Image: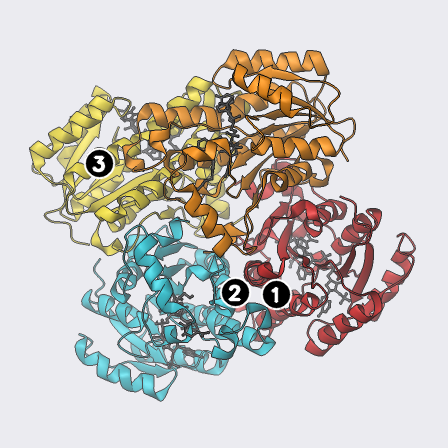
Chain colours: A cyan, B red, C orange, D yellow
Amino acid sequence: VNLENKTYVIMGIANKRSIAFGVAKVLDQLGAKLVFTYRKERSRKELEKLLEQLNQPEAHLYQIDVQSDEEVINGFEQIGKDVGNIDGVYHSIAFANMEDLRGRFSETSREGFLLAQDISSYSLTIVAHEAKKLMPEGGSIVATTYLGGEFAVQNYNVMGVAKASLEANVKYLALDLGPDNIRVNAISAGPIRTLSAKGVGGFNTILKEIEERAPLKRNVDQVEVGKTAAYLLSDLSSGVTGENIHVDSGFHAIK
Amino acid sequence: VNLENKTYVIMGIANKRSIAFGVAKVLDQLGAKLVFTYRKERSRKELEKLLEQLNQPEAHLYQIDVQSDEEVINGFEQIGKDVGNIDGVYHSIAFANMEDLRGRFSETSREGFLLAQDISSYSLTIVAHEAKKLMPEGGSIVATTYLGGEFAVQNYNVMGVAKASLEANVKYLALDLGPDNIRVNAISAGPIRTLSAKGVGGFNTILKEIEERAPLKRNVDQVEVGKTAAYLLSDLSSGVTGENIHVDSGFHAIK
Amino acid sequence: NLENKTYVIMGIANKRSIAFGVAKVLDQLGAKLVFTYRKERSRKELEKLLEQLNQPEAHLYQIDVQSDEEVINGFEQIGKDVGNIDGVYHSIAFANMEDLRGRFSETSREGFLLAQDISSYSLTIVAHEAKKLMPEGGSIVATTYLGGEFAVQNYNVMGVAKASLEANVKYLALDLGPDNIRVNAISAGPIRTLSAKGVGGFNTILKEIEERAPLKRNVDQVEVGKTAAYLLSDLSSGVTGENIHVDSGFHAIK
Amino acid sequence: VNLENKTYVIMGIANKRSIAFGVAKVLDQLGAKLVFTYRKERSRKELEKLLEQLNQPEAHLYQIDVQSDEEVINGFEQIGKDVGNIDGVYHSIAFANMEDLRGRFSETSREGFLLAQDISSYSLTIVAHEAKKLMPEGGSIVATTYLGGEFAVQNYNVMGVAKASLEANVKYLALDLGPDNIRVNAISAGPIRTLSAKGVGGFNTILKEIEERAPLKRNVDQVEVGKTAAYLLSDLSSGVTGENIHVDSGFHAIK
Ligand SMILES: NC(=O)c1ccc[n+]([C@@H]2O[C@H](COP(=O)([O-])OP(=O)(O)OC[C@H]3O[C@@H](n4cnc5c(N)ncnc54)[C@H](OP(=O)(O)O)[C@@H]3O)[C@@H](O)[C@H]2O)c1
Ligand SMILES: NC(=O)c1ccc[n+]([C@@H]2O[C@H](COP(=O)([O-])OP(=O)(O)OC[C@H]3O[C@@H](n4cnc5c(N)ncnc54)[C@H](OP(=O)(O)O)[C@@H]3O)[C@@H](O)[C@H]2O)c1
Ligand SMILES: NC(=O)c1ccc[n+]([C@@H]2O[C@H](COP(=O)([O-])OP(=O)(O)OC[C@H]3O[C@@H](n4cnc5c(N)ncnc54)[C@H](OP(=O)(O)O)[C@@H]3O)[C@@H](O)[C@H]2O)c1
Ligand SMILES: NC(=O)c1ccc[n+]([C@@H]2O[C@H](COP(=O)([O-])OP(=O)(O)OC[C@H]3O[C@@H](n4cnc5c(N)ncnc54)[C@H](OP(=O)(O)O)[C@@H]3O)[C@@H](O)[C@H]2O)c1
Ligand SMILES: CCCCCCc1ccc(Oc2ccccc2C#N)c(O)c1
Ligand SMILES: CCCCCCc1ccc(Oc2ccccc2C#N)c(O)c1
Ligand SMILES: CCCCCCc1ccc(Oc2ccccc2C#N)c(O)c1
Ligand SMILES: CCCCCCc1ccc(Oc2ccccc2C#N)c(O)c1
Ligand SMILES: N[C@@H](CCC(=O)O)C(=O)O
Ligand SMILES: N[C@@H](CCC(=O)O)C(=O)O
Ligand SMILES: N[C@@H](CCC(=O)O)C(=O)O
């Protein structure tokens, strides 16, 4: 593309291995102004250190726990006060407990099921609503999903149902904001070594299955997700909404 | 398909228009012993009255609000004490607040979003968990979904996202409970005038458009969901699990 | 219960045909069965297989679906010999052996069109002809494989023919629905049939299903026929343009 | 997405309105070298006049009728001799007789059905086989489909079954050629006023409905298909294969 004079909000960089950091690098390289949101003080610390590798002349950092309507509302409001209107949001946030992930799915607790939904799916809805106010002439919103939202994948358990929820959330949001010229899409990333990935049982062996079985016979990386993100966040993908692009070496397409 | 010496639990008859009552008439007509569960007082009364149409020699009625683990745990425990091992469960339960079935999806409240997940999806997981205890030999579990879980349908809003979640729940339950010989499937019913259908904006429209546009050129009814449920709840459908069967006059197949 | 129901069953070759699984189940449910075979060999064979069933008579018709006239005259005769029918079970497909292994991208025009012709287009002509014999509606069921939905190694040109057959179903459903003819697919798991010898690495798939499918076991022709009973009968009123996976749950997992 | 020192074969321009000339304008814009294939001498004459609006310094025009193995085989071979190694093929080719694009699908002739399959689906397979010869390094093949491939759309009839075939063709080519680093994907375009769209009953109606019912509330144009083509044919889409991107204002996602 080329993304000068554009401003994107990126949510969910924890460290250098975060998918959303792959997005950040690509967008930053393409001329975009970036604004970053985080939950833990530690993620902010990592952000401050990761910005040195970037071209951003300014640190634009905001603490937003997507569990709190107040923090999302006040965050996006302060972002508009600081940078003005924006062109899109990359959503890269999910959560579930260990204790429910390494259960039989049937043994999942209600509080863990809903926690997963709340952070991993609902949060897009409220982010979309608040971000929309900073997009008076339209823009783009991308969330990150995984194929365990379309099929039942051993171990992914509660997070699979939260992804199914997220992928519909995208479709309903696309229907709703469409007339506002806001596009909403999902990237279905293949497995990537991240901090959150350490929490999913059997991650390593799925990695390996991908190399053996996927059409491109290899795994993907954060920058690949970031390149597809730039497509979805740019004018290149006008006409595309409610879509789910698999960035996964073609693994979605086989059995 | 003869069901004598089978026992099924049917969840979510409110009145004679309920989908689950379509299911009950079919199962009863085929010789099954039936247990029913309800939430409201008013629903148990309706059930008491509706039983006079059935061949069920006794009434097995249980109050189970699926918002409560204790009620589901204790309910299914009582069922096992009163009737013994069962052969399957029909789940016909969902809820969302009125203002979440119309206007704009992007303005869905967090509590409204999570409420719909809890009742309309999570409840399957917990029901399957407890119903399993009564199926040492294997059995069958069916839940009721709608096309709006697969596609954004105007006005179906927060329920669309809960049916997406429910549909994934079915897949993950099938994967989990499969080795125990417990099948888990969905019926995706077409629009049908029920009490809950009154909370969905634009329902009359969707009905007409089915008559005009679906293959069979006519809407379905509860008995037709019922005969598909009989198939899934019986040995006719051994080998079928994690499936979603559209009983919607072919509407799912066109565009 | 299918008493005074009459169904045409296409593609029995031997005791292991999926269509024989369907036959036994329908026969068991009291239905009258007409069979269609392709070459005289399957005739002496079929004749022997029906000594198992409860059919009082052999209604047996050679139809190679590569010929319009054999499909046209075939159904025309069935109507004269037996009267109106209640549905059709399609259990028919073909591809040349060299196209069912190695490299899809190396498939010949002729071998690709052959597969389309027999495995997909034949449904359309069968439906048009069979419709003439179901004035009050009826039910048509074809057999597919998950390979028409996902690319499955080795299945190759047959996967593109099945994808074709699954859309044919959709389109037959839309077109024939106002006549009350329902059209559906059963997507069967793998089963040791005569024709599955020709698919590369079929034994490797058989074992994957056992290891990985929700039911942790494979399916048989009888389970396929039980689901065909549902689809061919009134139990499945309301359901058309559908593809039901009788596959120990394999389609739902990745 | 800068495409200098890239070369793409664009198959199936007939006039200023062709979807493939959308692609061409876009790829040309981004600095690619372009090679055109046509069938009818009139499509060459049209290409020659449209070349004047491109920045291409030379005309590279081949006559390939994809019904001929020999013509595909010799066309591509020749292309290799003339411009050397290519980066991708954009396939924008389909055909069906007018009878079989209206009225009753069940009345499709054998001959019409195979003719649609041959031109509209099989051609991709042989084009990929021959084009693989000019991509020893890897590359990108994109074919043009329509939602009629995934659902029954009234009137689309024999072509929809041909587009199903094509979409599956894309999936199998992606499995087969992934190990050679050749990505194969499909763009599912919304309805667009072209020469070949004049053959399809009820085309005007579908246009109007997309406007009323699709999330963006507008039709897409050829240039929007080109912008997404540029993405699929470039490194921006490096982890994407066996995929189908709907450039259709959202329509695919709604029911
Ligand atoms: N890695 C993969 O294999 C893979 C594959 C497909 C899809 N995905 C999806 O990709 C996205 C990014 O995950 P990742 O793999 O990049 O892992 P990650 O680096 O661990 O990032 C996850 C992010 O989620 C944020 N988060 C969790 N709860 C939050 C909350 N309540 N409020 C605000 N932020 C919250 C974390 O912030 P804090 O650390 O500050 O708490 C962290 O930045 C997730 O949606 C994941 O499900 C990942
Ligand atoms: N009608 C349609 O067009 C349609 C189409 C597709 C799918 N569906 C689905 O079919 C199922 C049955 O709905 P329906 O149309 O038959 O409407 P219905 O008659 O209103 O039944 C809904 C039932 O859900 C029960 N329920 C709600 N919350 C509950 C809770 N917390 N605990 C226990 N029970 C609870 C209700 O019980 P109480 O009244 O006692 O509170 C009522 O029995 C639902 O899953 C619905 O989403 C309906
Ligand atoms: N077995 C599996 O794992 C599997 C799984 C999923 C789907 N299927 C499908 O199930 C169906 C039945 O196959 P099967 O596995 O049961 O194998 P089968 O016993 O070999 O039956 C296949 C039948 O197709 C008939 N046939 C082929 N071309 C014909 C033509 N041109 N005209 C008339 N009949 C023709 C064969 O006839 P002749 O012997 O007379 O040549 C044979 O009766 C096929 O559609 C197959 O694609 C099979
Ligand atoms: N327009 C739409 O709404 C729409 C929507 C989605 C997808 N599509 C698809 O987009 C692609 C391009 O179509 P279009 O709408 O842009 O129509 P178009 O401008 O009429 O182009 C169709 C092209 O197909 C070529 N063609 C037909 N048979 C051929 C053969 N045997 N060998 C070589 N070329 C052949 C034609 O070449 P000649 O004129 O020289 O014969 C023509 O250039 C097709 O796959 C179509 O199915 C169209
Ligand atoms: C067997 C599983 C296959 C590998 C899964 C690939 C994958 C890895 C990490 C993911 O991220 C999370 C996972 C669980 C809980 C929170 C997050 C977060 N954030 C994800 O969504 C998907
Ligand atoms: C967009 C209009 C399409 C017509 C929708 C068909 C339909 C009607 C009623 C349904 O039931 C509920 C709906 C909302 C809340 C609770 C329940 C319950 N129980 C349902 O799930 C689907
Ligand atoms: C790697 C794939 C695993 C096994 C696939 C299961 C399968 C077995 C047999 C099939 O039948 C045919 C196959 C080829 C040609 C004709 C027929 C016929 N008739 C089929 O369609 C699918
Ligand atoms: C029911 C109307 C649906 C709207 C149609 C969208 C559409 C328009 C034109 C298309 O192109 C062809 C159509 C038929 C035959 C050849 C070609 C070619 N080339 C296409 O594939 C799809
Ligand atoms: N993370 C480990 C532990 C999972 C478990 O034992 O449940 C794995 O790859 O499975
Ligand atoms: N149930 C009425 C009211 C809709 C509304 O305005 O919310 C309908 O949509 O026809
Ligand atoms: N072009 C006409 C076709 C006319 C017909 O098939 O009757 C239409 O828009 O349908």
The correct choice, above or below, for A250 with respect to C63 in the image is below
Label 2 CB sits under 8 Å from any ligand 5 atom: no
Q: Nearer the viewer, residue D36 or B141?
A: B141
Under mark 1, the amino acid is Ser
Q: Position of residue B108 (x, y in %)?
A: 55, 69
Q: Are marks 1 and 2 in contact (CB under 8 Å)?
A: yes
Q: Nearer the viewer, residue C179 or A32?
A: C179
Q: CA distance from mark 2 to mark 3?
A: 42 Å
Residue visible at 11% across and 34% down in the picture: D80
Q: Nearer the viewer, residue D121 or A109?
A: A109
Determine which residue is flagged by label 3: D10
The residue drawn where x is 47% and y is 46% is C206
Q: Which residue is mark 2?
A: A161
Q: Chain of mark 2?
A: A
User: Which residue occupies the foreground of this view, B205 or C67?
Assistant: C67
Q: Secondary structure at mark 1?
A: helix
